[PDB]
Amino acid sequence: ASAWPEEKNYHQPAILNSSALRQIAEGTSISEMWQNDLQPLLIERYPGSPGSYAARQHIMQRIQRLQADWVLEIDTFLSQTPYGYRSFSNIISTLNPTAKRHLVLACHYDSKYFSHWNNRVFVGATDSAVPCAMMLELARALDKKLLSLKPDLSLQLIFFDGEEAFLHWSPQDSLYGSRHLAAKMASTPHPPGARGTSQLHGMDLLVLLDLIGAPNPTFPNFFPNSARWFERLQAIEHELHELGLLKDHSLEGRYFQNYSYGGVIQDDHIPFLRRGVPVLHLIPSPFPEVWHTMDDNEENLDESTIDNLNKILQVFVLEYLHL
Ligand SMILES: Cc1cncn1Cc1ccccc1
Ligand SMILES: [Zn+2]
Image (cartoon, rainbow, N blue to C red):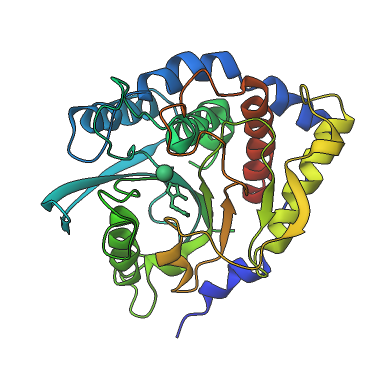
């Protein structure tokens, strides 16, 4: 049939030079991210809540003000939960929806459901309000360079709804939005008119951000087949450090360690991984100390660590896109 689905296997980056790295490092404002992209999301936003619709409106609005031609679809669906049927809505933002291949950035925008505890409200700053904000910032910071898109490859953002369990993590109570969107893409022909290939095939690489925002994260390399792209993240961290472009950062405590994890951490990528999508899982091990506590808030975030990772990520995306 069609073998384009193999191009991602042979795709190679266009490594940036020191002058361009500097540019990128200069091009991203951590403090504008914090005010315009991050703070509006630090609300209770479990699926079906008022905050979910708010968070959903804020993500679409911030994406809309940008010059690049983002197409936004709200993939709304119904699914059974421990509390009955409920409605969920994934946010999908795509440049050039026609192109066969797309590099995918994503995270979950729901917050785990938890009634008030000690009069406190769970807002999951690292899980995953910050990954959401890093995605919005990457799109703003790279707006002009992405506008250049009008190799048949472009960029897609996915903000999954319903990553978290409502009552008890299990295969039927978890990954609502990603289980839905992976099965939908696996059976939607791509590109338009194709007779043998799916959108799931068009996913060049799924870069899943989760649990980012704490100090000193250590990201393992999880998969033998995306290991080379993990190595680019290592390389980019190193060079930005040597060029004085990172803050409060030591090579003794670098983010992208040279160690592998022999297993898997259940997350929104599992539905795509099982169907053969390559994944770069940017989740740290161990998890933040504030994981699933009421302390996973704004005050326990580390501003420098997010700034640094924004720069590493933005470099990675431009190098993947040859921009
Ligand atoms: C990655 C994540 C973020 N929030 C929940 N998960 C899922 C999970 C993974 C391992 C153990 C418990 C729960
Ligand atoms: Zn969680």
